[PDB]
Length: 432
Image 1 (cartoon, helix red, strand yellow):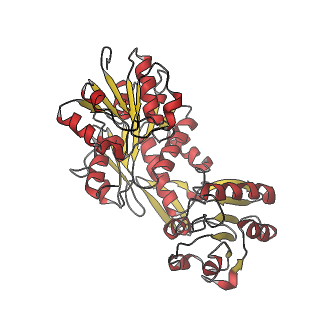
Image 2: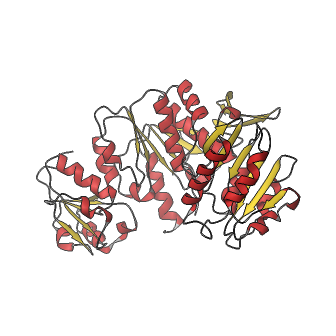
């Protein structure tokens, strides 16, 4: 698209709005920028020559615009933006600008849960294939920064807010991974369904009807599911396989992530990569080497047959339940639980903690509550570090050390990231 001569106004001075400033300056267009915050992050990164307005939206600037570029977020609901819309002024977001310029195929991923892991995995599948891939769309990697004539494939994580302002996306493969519960379910799902418009292949969740295109499945659709679908899980003879169009393609034991929802993330990623034309061989290889995003079933150490897993992002019971359901451990699971349980009901975890192959190490404010899940195999300490030093002498090849604590960290830690980083530091000391 040609923006020369246009009066361009950008709303938002986060990284996304900054990437929009860079985009227009590179094309000889000087935009104006505004942010309702008095001192947004990006303010001190702006070129001096870009006019800026902070502390409110400047309606005089908006109503005089030829093009408004709105950063995604609750800010899209601002009345000043509605008034501009009411007057017929064109409003787009950064992903719209990107799609107008992209010269390589786009894989587009949205959903309520798992969208970061699946996006990252598809990126790793492309990298294993030797493809010059651009991975982004998350808050920290604005899509416009990825635009490059040498890029061979883009893989984008998209939000509902981003999709609300995007009209030109024509993905080679697109998915809504799942829909669960800022606004009502109904606006939330409508935005997500836009991801399939003009998509060459739609990858749907066979177990979640809200991921199906508005008209339903059509000849563009491939599904992933737990028991059923084009891509699904096959349990037989005590083993579990990824199965694709009726053929076993990978024993899940060759992967480093486990847990059922990580297996379906793997299936969704493989379906996207297949549909984008990436080689099956390298996509499966990437599944065997992927070690996870920070704090999200992250393999922080594998040594002497023991795998140390940082799942500190599990701050509630549902997240730990998902780590445990379908978990694979050859030997003994050493499970670290504890922190501030927020007076939660921990009983859903009980069905997973039976057997001769589970030890619990419980710490933090509510550690005694967690140890009560099964006291005969549980130890209680004040701190995570004490629990780790207690278990380190006991681990043997085949074992897993899993920090999936089902609790908030805030009784002893600044946040779950600090908790996970401390786990990784101590794993390296005690397991190397």
